[PDB]
Length: 30
Image (cartoon, rainbow, N blue to C red; front, top):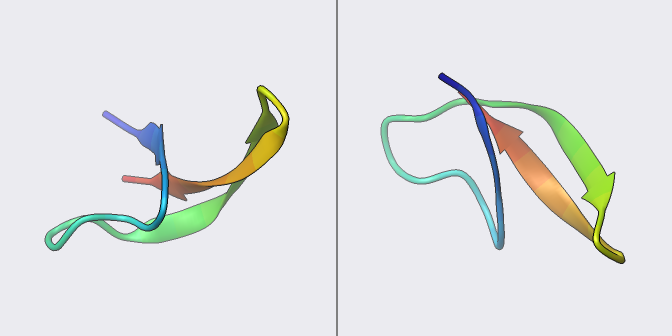
């Protein structure tokens, strides 16, 4: 399962991209 997160992906997740919604950028993390 993947999630959008700020400020960064948590340890144990990998960043696969950037989410752009609710007015800000998020890390897309899986």
